[PDB]
Image (cartoon, rainbow over all chains, first blue to last red; front, side, top):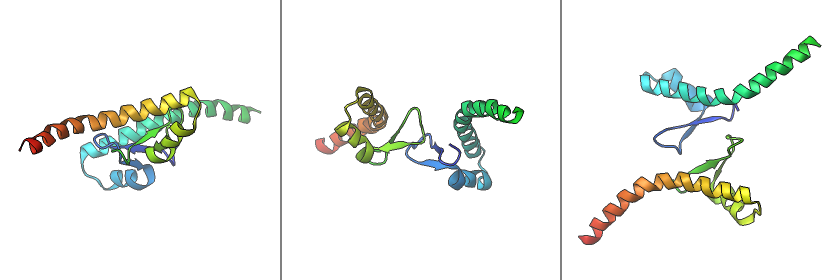
Length: 68
Length: 68
């Protein structure tokens, strides 16, 4: 989900950006407030939700591996 | 929008299908009712909305070209 998840433009939904090219070069180069807030939030929300459920399950398990 | 618009799976949103490979081979080969209803509706809705506004504008214009 981290390496292949992408984020699509709201006004042109056919151009979707992966994180490592395109979305990292927005946050490292842009000086526009609205373009930086878009990337952030978007990527955030999406990957967020995903890693969420999985993360919870993972936390629950990795504790059983450590307590044993 | 027609040639580059894609449709993503609901349970795995990282696999997205274009129309000409993948989405045409669902409707031509599958015998599953729920997989055929998914493709249809999805593609439909998306391309639908897009071509919608543009289509209206286009209809409005092409009439001025024909009346002149």
